[PDB]
Amino acid sequence: MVKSKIGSWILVLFVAMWSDVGLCKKRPKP
Image 1 (tube, rainbow, N blue to C red):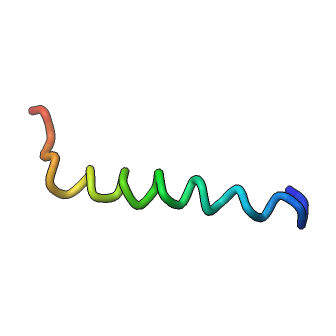
Image 2: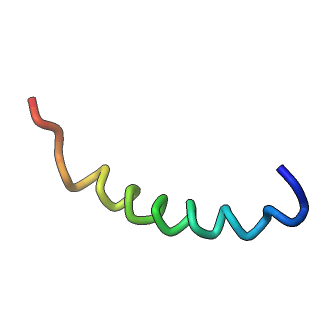
């Protein structure tokens, strides 16, 4: 968005890193 809104990815980063670990290990439902 703006150069001022650069410290927002860091957030989505953490949630991304976690959501990442919860991909290849959580296994599918079906």
